[PDB]
Amino acid sequence: TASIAQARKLVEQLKMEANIDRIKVSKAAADLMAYCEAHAKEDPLLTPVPASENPFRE
Amino acid sequence: VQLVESGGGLVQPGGSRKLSCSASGFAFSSFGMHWVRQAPEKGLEWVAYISSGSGTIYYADTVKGRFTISRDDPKNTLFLQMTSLRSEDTAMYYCVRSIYYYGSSPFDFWGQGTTLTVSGSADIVMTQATSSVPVTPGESVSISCRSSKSLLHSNGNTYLYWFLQRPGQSPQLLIYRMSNLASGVPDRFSGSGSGTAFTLTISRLEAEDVGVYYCMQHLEYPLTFGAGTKLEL
Amino acid sequence: CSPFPLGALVPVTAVCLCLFVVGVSGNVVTVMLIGRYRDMRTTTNLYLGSMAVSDLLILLGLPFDLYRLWRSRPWVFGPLLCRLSLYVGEGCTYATLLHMTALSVERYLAICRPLRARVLVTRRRVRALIAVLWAVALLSAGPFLFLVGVEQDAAALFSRECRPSPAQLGALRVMLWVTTAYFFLPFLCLSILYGLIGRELWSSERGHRQTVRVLLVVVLAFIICWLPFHVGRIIYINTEDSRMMYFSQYFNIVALQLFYLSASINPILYNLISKKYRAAAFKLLL
Amino acid sequence: ELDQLRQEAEQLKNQIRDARKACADATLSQITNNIDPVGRIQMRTRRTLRGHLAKIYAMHWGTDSRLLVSASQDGKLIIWDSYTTNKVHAIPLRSSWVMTCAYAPSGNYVACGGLDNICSIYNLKTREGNVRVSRELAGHTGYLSCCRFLDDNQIVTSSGDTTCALWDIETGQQTTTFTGHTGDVMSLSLAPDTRLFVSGACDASAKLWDVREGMCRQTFTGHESDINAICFFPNGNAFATGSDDATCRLFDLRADQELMTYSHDNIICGITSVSFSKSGRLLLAGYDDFNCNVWDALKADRAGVLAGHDNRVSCLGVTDDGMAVATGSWDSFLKIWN
Amino acid sequence: CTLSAEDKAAVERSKMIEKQLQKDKQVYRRTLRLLLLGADNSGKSTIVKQMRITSGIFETKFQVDKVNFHMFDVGAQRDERRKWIQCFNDVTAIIFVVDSSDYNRLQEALNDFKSIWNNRWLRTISVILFLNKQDLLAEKVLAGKSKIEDYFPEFARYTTPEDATPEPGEDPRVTRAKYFIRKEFVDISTASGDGRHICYPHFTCSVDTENARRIFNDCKDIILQMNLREYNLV
Ligand SMILES: Cc1cc(N(C)C(=O)[C@H]2CC[C@H](Oc3cccc(CO)c3)CC2)ccc1CN1CCN[C@@H](C)C1
Ligand SMILES: CC(C)CCC[C@@H](C)[C@H]1CC[C@H]2[C@@H]3CC=C4C[C@@H](O)CC[C@]4(C)[C@H]3CC[C@]12C
């Protein structure tokens, strides 16, 4: 039937999403903060640039 | 893409003539049209320009009050009615399509042209120091051309165009806005320069890369052309 | 002229204060609600805002015209201030008349022809029409920019009123009849056009009653306010004999009362009844 | 049999949750509390695009930060030269109801679609000099909600049939199809490397898929309402999503769980679009209350507000260089801040 | 000005595009928009075909009294409706077709009408109820094989209105059934309306040719009410 096929496909899918290496949230936090800090000096929106350097304002 | 022109022939001094150019294969209402004249064994000279939708019309000083230009959009036709023709007007006349916008490429198509026979203060002086430099296939070449004024605009675009008139053919856009390479042209060709001095380099010359090379401005409406630099086999 | 007795003069002053307060409150509230929001800034609401500011300018004429009444003729504000009194008042009155008739025309076009015909109405058209109507109103008061005010006759504490020169009266008379058309032209517009509108909303109940009752009340208020104004202006410009002056001064007391009443009631009649303006007020003020 | 498989799925879900809580060692708020505040940000409208007749619904910046593509339900695609407020191109659409539009990075191709159920791709540099129908991709059995370009020969499209399709423009065929989603897919985003992509659906679920393998590598279920937008962190290892529940949730692919939540009491409406700046510290999210809010991605605090609108903030996007932000609304008005 | 030659040409092209957009707006605004919905058992397709004489959207132009009308039908989009219905905001009317002849699934159509009426997006848009399939309903009521009392227990208590004007040559039972269906639908529509939007039910048949005129009249009444709202008259 369709029910058995759908159930087996779902079970196999959950297996694939479960048996995978994962890292701790602290590492992800550190990496994201490092990326933001390193590129914090290259984001005009966060750090406004001088009007001479603003294409949208002379 | 097809531009076929007619109306060139033998004329008398003081009479008027009518040049008709039919366009097919591309939209004619969205393309500005330029009429250009080249005297026999001479360089290209700009006659007139008309923008899309009969919006803007601009002539040259020598043809002010004598030449008139019009465009029949539904028929995709261009009419040049010129009066008081004289011995100075004999030339090959080309109709050139041009499109203007960010990332555009004007002067990209040229008509075959019509042969017409009859019996600088404010302009940018487009110099071409090189006149005739023979060169061989397989050898890199470069040609430099200057200007009276720094062509670089506040925009950042340097309005310098490079064309090639291969022997017995109409001119072909090679490079637009000083560095951008036109569609269908080999990457051997490359253009560089600064405000008042520009250069065109052909990496590996070939038989196809032989002809006169012209350098044109695009700041002032006169749209003055360069003198020319021939290449030999 | 001879100042009125205490009599009904003091009650007239009191009613003047009441109408002044009511009109300024209503017009200021309207102008605010149209400036502090955006859904209430439509073409119709723009006409109402123009009318509201014009009516505020009119009501600002209350203290000077009340001074010339409570106080007798002696005028000390100078030819310039009197001149400006009569010019700003006339211009604002005629601008509001033009705005009312234009609103009537727009209502007729949009309402009597909901899908019979659609005339596209753009913001630019409404702005240009407002500018043109105001310019026409001001220029129609242009003769009063060259034909009013001579106070020179003890010479300062008992000087003459801001009357026109005797011979100059001639010119004045002509204008006071030209402006009579400004009564007849909107009237024909309002009674006819709204008439047709009332025909559509009665030839088709809960909601199409209230609209055709507000339109009738608006027309009646229009006649009540604006007819005595012009009637009395012409009576005053034919003040040949003393009893004509008496009749004119008292009738024109009544006419001033009704005219400033018109300014008081315009926002209530036109804006308050509308659900959009009422809701916006219930928001900005509660 | 069915009961056994259902119980196995339940056990696998419980194992997933247990592993997540095992790796849920700490929160970003604890770690990020030592980061200096971003502070008040004063973003003011820098450019207004006015030439549209109806609701604006989709917009995506190309490789450059100058050209802007916008799609309007009047049935029109407009390419504007943002620096000069010039309509570079105007293209009528065979279907008036348009909801998605994508810009190829090279700029030679543009794509869009809507309730027509067929994705339309045109090109700007035709030899004829006019825009023409380059491709008409068909096969989706539901509205096209989003679409994105891997390159000039590949295009990803999300539709309401609970299935997403990667197509080849050369042959106009469904190169790959994913049917793992349960709810309607609303938005699509592309990872930097393009080897992976993440989608969000109305089932309150986001899913990560491989472009070539095409299997649901990971799933995220942290929302309580339909998801309207999806955007990936610039580094490509994390993403953020917003739903009608009036909150935003940012997840990390590597940890396979939620990382942070952004919301406040006053906001009581859904989310339209979410995006990140070049640094990623500024998370700009649209709203249905005529407003957009830019928050501190790390510290999760209100940094700035864009209130220059008269209707829904249907779409919002950031440029490649991050020099400005564009916002399109239901009132046919496009506003660009910086 | 500082614009270079090639910038002024682009500006000229931009102004030309602006004028073309103005022309397109002129063409667009003169027409009225209708979103048409119903079920397979409902006579949707025949209604659409008569008005004329895997795409997810079907468009139909029709002119009534020199007025253009868009009619938009959604057939291939999935059963879910709350998501793709936002696109059809600012549509002058929503023509909902209900199979008045079908008694078994009338409850589901009634619930669907409830859901559409309660839609927050469609709170300022008018709905026209076309109770299609009126000859079939007439025969079904006349025969007596299928009774509406079983499906709707309150039909027994319901009575034929005295103010009602029965159609010529109409038997009392058919009129009572039609008025009961219309009464239920009107009761649902009135709730939560608060005057923001008005419903316009009408008895329509598969072969009836008055659909165009009825739609035009309803979309004229809707426009009149909207103008009353905007022009400060109500
Ligand atoms: C209704 C009213 C009555 C009076 N009162 C108490 C009067 O006694 C008379 C009334 C007739 C008026 O006759 C003239 C009209 C115009 C110009 C001149 C130049 O002589 C004379 C002279 C004064 C004052 C002001 C107003 C309202 N005003 C608002 C501003 N605009 C003015 C026209 C109307
Ligand atoms: C959101 C946009 C479209 C609203 C623009 C407001 C326009 C339509 C309206 C609102 C108030 C108006 C002003 C009100 C009063 C006057 C005095 C008159 O002597 C000259 C015109 C002038 C100065 C009007 C100009 C137009 C105006 C500014």
Image (spheres, coloured by chain):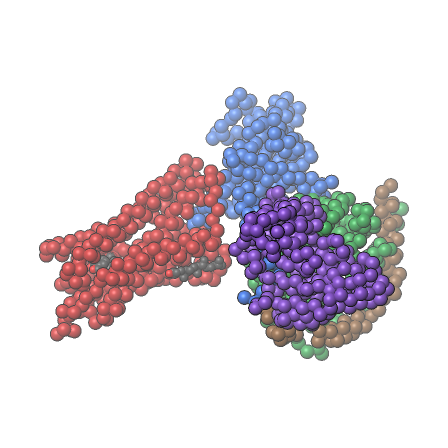
Chain colours: A brown, B purple, C red, D green, E blue
Q: Position of residue E89 (x, y in %)?
A: 59, 48
Residue under the image location 31 percent in, 55 percent down:
C94
Q: Quadrant of ligand 1?
A: bottom left
In the image, residue E77 sits, relative to residue C84, either above or below, namely above
| Image quadrant assignment for residue B77 | top right
Q: Residue B150 placed where, x, y %?
A: 64, 71
- Relative to B203, E104 lies left or right: left
Viewed as shown, does residue C91 lie left or right of D214?
left
Q: Residue at x 67, y 42 (%)?
A: E57
Residue that protrudes farthest toward the front in the picture: B119
Q: Nearer the viewer, residue C17 or D79?
A: D79
- Residue A45 visible to the viewer: no
Question: Residue drawn at (71%, 70%), measured in percent from left and top?
Answer: B129
Residue in view at x 68 percent, y 78 percent: D36
Question: In front: C127, or D166?
Answer: C127
- Asked where in the image residue C18 lies, by quadrant, the reply is bottom left
Q: How many marks do you count on the picture?
A: 0
Q: Quick one: quadrant of the N terminus of chain E?
A: bottom right
Judge by depth and name the residue closer to the eye, E24 or E58: E24
B183 or A43, nearer to the observer: B183
**E220 relative position to E150: left or right:** left
Depicted E166 relative to depicted D201: above or below: above
